[PDB]
Image (cartoon, coloured by chain):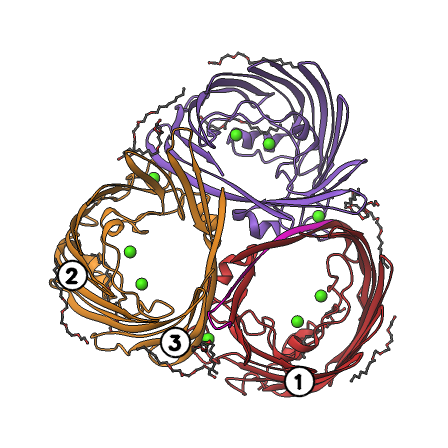
Chain colours: A red, B purple, C orange
């Protein structure tokens, strides 16, 4: 079976200096089936991703049963699969100054590429959830060695609370050229009625020149070394009637390179029927950074 | 909600010297919704446009209410939105020698580009219609200055007749490099039963080197100047049973560069069920020009 | 009318030296209609082919009636349209060492390209079938001369047996640069209940440097000459319950260049509901060649 859904948005976005019109529309194909014994299977991708979905680079394919779910393609890594992101600000998703996304080390297109899908396994039973993910270590479908990513995460929900932890790592094919990386995460999520609170703390080490590129800094001409880092953040959103209001703040601190605090604040108003008016403000504390903002409408179909 | 429709065509096309097979198929995604108070919203794009629809370059998104309709993306400019084009000739739409399209100055991909949608506002009440359109003046979603287009048009229907006028303009970011342009249009449309008649007259001024490029002439190495131009045309089509027969003639006259008269004549025969046999002939009076022609079938799905 | 269907696959594939994850998903658009007198028409293409389907390069458009069926776009040539391919091995279709496809000389993207569809005509009456195909001889929709392909084939079914023959040819635009080519085929297909047997023999001549490129050999710097070739193969597959087992062997023998025997063996297990577990092995006898293999699941939607 093949089902269709879609979304679209239109409005004005401020890039720090000028306003521009910003709009888009997308269609999602959701495909599903069930075998004779009740294993469920499916696949999905968006219309603008159709070339990539044909090589494994975009979209996902899955098989699930009593054993849990196996998904291959452009999949999330294990930690992101269980804890997600902080409150999304602005109708265009204003990630220009850092954004709402939590800084996971693996999955979500870190190594996914043409002819190179990644794997995500999930399982839940009651109150508990576990996820595990990995890439295959070879470029495309070739025999050339690639960096290889892997992660494992577990969560437990008790009442209003889910708490969890994840561990992620990237193994370098050549540690003279790129240091191995790893990150450990603790995440907590709480709903107190109309209010959602999400918080995380992450700690680990990154390749030096990969870390410098986060801050848009040229690499140093030396053999690869690792730098220690930490990241933590929080978001709060609450709904009163048709109005949701929310925001987040995150800081990323990489030893010997730099630190940044980035944040955003936005609101939406539900018009019903799949339409909402959405606007927001986002920034970070780096020297140059002017605040980005937007105001428009989002539609679901 | 997401609906599907499509079209396809196949036949033989003569390019002035040789015949070639010419065929295509397309799918249109039409998405729609209604808010709780009855504002209607939607989006559409074709499958071959899906990459562009995701940045605002192709397809359109709209919101309408009692106030009229706001559309953003790859939109028509205000004059084209109210008066359209002359009778379309040939199953492949034989625009090779000039074509049936009326020469509007703005909208319809004049400035629309990646991350750069344009805006069209329309409103009707009874017998009267107004449209207004503009681009935002900045390249992409950047702060780089772009040419900016704008147009306004109004029409009035009285019986068999709609008459209207439009005014369009493009403001140059640097008039040493490209002159400002403007065009005023008068259009009339009349249906006399099975017969449709459409006529327009346009007058204004164009950038010199933009005008020379219409006639495929190299630019002159001097500071930009403006040239005066006029354009006018007429088409007639009539239906008798399953057969429609029609044609058009247009002339474009640009002062100090050149003039051209271009025309076409074609027919279609409806087979019912969404299929028709369509063929046509088109040419212009320039020196080289051999007549283009085609014959094939068009399908709607 | 527009209908949707799709497919997806995921598993592990061995390239001769290493295992890699390999997955994809696709959506097919099938469009159909009927005229008032009952001529049927349609078009189809897959979502990843939507750009190509808009110029004639990918997908097909057709019209059929009592006269047979005319199809234009990315069509099969006449022989492939009647006799098909040998048993397909592996969930990824392991064609890496030669594959299951029968080596037809024309159609199936030999000359199909942007703005350049090819034509396939088919007709059946009772026990007999005929097909005829051709390209138009001009590059794109231009007047530049291209190689031109053509083929004719006929088949007759009597009981469990279909036997047939086809003749295919490519006319070179310049025989100093590329020799003319031709191939004659005899094919037989037999179903003996759960068992399918397909066999063919082909004989003809190929351009020298086109033949050398099959074996990945550099061209010779001389005026084009033709080399004689023969190809023949067989496949057998049988189904017992949910299990199909099958394989094929083909040899290609080009005089003065080289010969190769390539083969594959695979199985599938139907899980019902549109899902199957599929795996296979394939190889050829050339010097370097290590065996390719895969194991995964295929889904239809
Ligand atoms: C020259 C400025 C052009 C600005 C064009 C904006 C196009 C997008 O429309 C959305 C703007 O956000 C505000 C809210 O619109 C929602 C409808 O009105 C509410 C009725 O209950
Ligand atoms: C553990 C891996 C973390 C990788 C993703 C981190 C994403 C963090 O967002 C950083 C936010 O800052 C934005 C970019 O910095 C460039 C700013 O311009 C420099 C001078 O103002
Ligand atoms: C297991 C979860 C533990 C999570 C603990 C950390 C959550 C709090 O960190 C939030 C960020 O630090 C706040 C201060 O930054 C202030 C300045 O930015 C301007 C905001 O307008
Ligand atoms: C806290 C949530 C709300 C954040 C709202 C941000 C403010 C947005 O409103 C201002 C819109 O006015 C800007 C100008 O429009 C520019 C149009 O571009 C066309 C130029 O000719
Ligand atoms: C070697 C020349 C090949 C030409 C191929 C033409 C393919 C397209 O078919 C359409 C041609 O236009 C003529 C009309 O066809 C309509 C069906 O016949 C009418 C029955 O009432
Ligand atoms: C007001 C803006 C008008 C811009 C669009 C005008 C489109 C007009 O069609 C012109 C028709 O002539 C075709 C092109 O000329 C090249 C012919 O080859 C030269 C020698 O034969
Ligand atoms: C407010 C609407 C006013 C419209 C007036 C103009 C309509 C007529 O112009 C049409 C073109 O001029 C006709 C002469 O060209 C003849 C030669 O071309 C060969 C045709 O086979
Ligand atoms: C006034 C409306 C009618 C316009 C009809 C134009 C004339 C079309 O009919 C002629 C078709 O015959 C041309 C040849 O077919 C070429 C096929 O290409 C394959 C070459 O091997
Ligand atoms: C680290 C190795 C990862 C391998 C991932 C394989 C992902 C694809 O799954 C398909 C493998 O083929 C075997 C059969 O799976 C079918 C389900 O089990 C049968 C229940 O009746
Ligand atoms: C009549 C036209 C035939 C054109 C298609 C033939 C396809 C045949 O498959 C050939 C199989 O061999 C694979 C390619 O050879 C390269 C191997 O590497 C060389 C040294 O091992
Ligand atoms: C009109 C149809 C006539 C078809 C006759 C030919 C069919 C048989 O040819 C098959 C291939 O030759 C078999 C020998 O190759 C053996 C070695 O390869 C290793 C297999 O594991
Ligand atoms: C005759 C039909 C059966 C052909 C089956 C081929 C054999 C397939 O099974 C072996 C799978 O085990 C291989 C290893 O998995 C590799 C995963 O890649 C991740 C590396 O970290
Ligand atoms: Ca985001
Ligand atoms: Ca992410
Ligand atoms: Ca790989
Ligand atoms: Ca046209
Ligand atoms: Ca136009
Ligand atoms: Ca812009
Ligand atoms: Ca194959
Ligand atoms: Ca083939
Ligand atoms: Ca051609």
Apparent side of residue A184 relative to residue C214 in the rendered image (left or right): right
Instruction: Find out whether residue B92 is within the magenta segment.
Output: no
Report the residue marked by disc 3. Answer: C295
How far apart marks 2 and 1 lie (CA) works out to: 57 Å
Apparent side of residue A200 relative to residue B15 in the rendered image (left or right): right
Is the C-beta separation of discs 1 and 3 under 8 Å? no
What secondary structure is the magenta-colored segment mainly?
A: strand
Instruction: Determine the chain carrying the residue at label 1.
Output: A
Is the C-beta separation of discs 3 and 2 under 8 Å? no
Q: Which mark is residue C182?
A: none
Residue A58 visible here: no
How many labels were placed on the picture? 3
Q: Give the label, 3 or 2, closer to the camera.
A: 3
**Residue A204 screen position, x and y as percent:** 68, 87
Does B257 appear above or below A108? above
**What's drawn in magenta, residue-wise?**
A21-39
Please tell me if label 3 and label 2 are on a single chain.
Answer: yes
């Amino acid at each position: 079976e093949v089902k269709l859904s879609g979304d679209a948005r239109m409005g004005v976005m401020y890039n720090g200096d000028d306003w521009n019109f910003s709009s888009r529309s997308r269609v999602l194909f959701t495909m599903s089936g069930t075998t004779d014994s009740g294993l469920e299977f499916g696949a999905s991708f968006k219309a603008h991703e159709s070339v990539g979905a044909e090589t494994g680079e975009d979209g996902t394919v899955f098989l699930s049963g009593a054993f849990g779910k196996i998904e291959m393609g452009d999949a999330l890594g294990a930690s992101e699969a269980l804890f997600g992101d902080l409150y999304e600000v602005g109708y265009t998703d204003l990630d220009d100054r850092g954004g709402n996304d939590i800084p996971y080390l693996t999955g979500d297109e870190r190594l996914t590429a043409e002819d190179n899908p990644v794997l995500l396994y999930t399982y839940s039973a009651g109150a508990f959830s576990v996820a595990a993910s990995m890439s295959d270590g070879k470029v495309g479908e070739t025999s050339e060695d690639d960096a290889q990513e892997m992660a494992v995460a577990a969560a437990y929900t008790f009442g209003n609370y889910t708490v969890g932890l994840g561990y992620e790592k990237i193994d370098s094919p050549d540690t003279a050229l790129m240091a191995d990386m790893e990150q450990l995460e603790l995440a907590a999520i709480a709903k107190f009625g109309a209010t959602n609170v999400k918080a995380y703390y992450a700690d680990g080490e990154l390749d030096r020149d990969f870390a410098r590129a986060v801050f848009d800094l040229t690499p140093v001409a030396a053999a690869a070394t690792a730098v220690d880092h930490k990241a933590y953040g929080l978001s709060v959103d609450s709904t009163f009637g048709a109005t949701t209001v929310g925001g987040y703040v995150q800081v990323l601190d990489i030893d010997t390179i730099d630190d940044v605090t980035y944040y955003g604040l936005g609101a939406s108003y539900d018009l019903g029927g799949g339409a909402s008016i959405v606007g927001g403000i986002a920034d970070n504390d780096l020297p140059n950074s002017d605040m980005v903002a937007d105001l428009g409408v989002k539609f679901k179909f």
